[PDB]
Length: 285
Ligand SMILES: [Cl-]
Image (cartoon, rainbow, N blue to C red; front, top):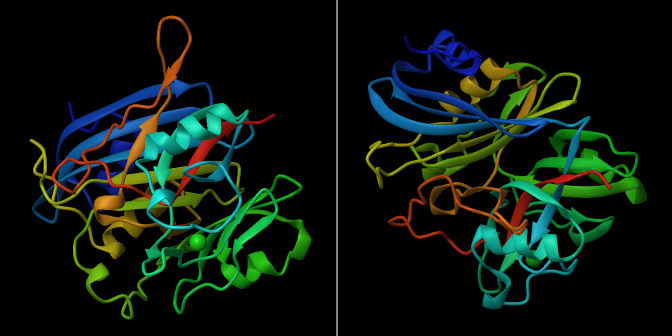
């Protein structure tokens, strides 16, 4: 019976998943597969989504609440993930999938990692330790790496979305999280990685804090990293987690208008958190 999908088999083979009770897969659209699973990780219940995106067919962009390419200005700058999708859509993008983005500091509200969008620097002054990045060059090539590597491309850097925690590096699971404090405990997680050829993107949304009938605890970073390598990530990074972790997909309603339902269970007692940046999978134009 279980597991029944390739990803389910990969996660069980990795040692990070047992007692699989849900293992479903669907096609969001051509070029985007979505897998939803429930299982135990060393005795603790979990509930995760893994999206596999064909980067020959689709691309990504970092997103803000209003699709404007300027730093956050205040509380108005944060909104639940669907708002980011709607604003991108209203500004000529066709959005198919989204997750929350990078870590933010407060007082004043400001992004902690590197943040570039459409060739415009939103932040180049990444905080201590906030070194991880998913980036794209103007030539269309996508990479996962370190902030200085992205910056070294100068005016050829198109997009950059920051993270905190390098999970997989050149096919080897990483475990150098010791400066990250309580982020090392189990948590909901959002993470992103690339295949070795950089033509496939993997997005994980790991629910946590047992806010629905799955009783999903959440994961440590070595466990998540191990799962990501298992499904094909050669390079992978941890984005903002906890109550920030949110997944949307496009739903085309009769009449043609899109909505952007949230598929996971937000860990702030089921209430979608207002987030200041995000990662959207969009059509190539
Ligand atoms: Cl900012």
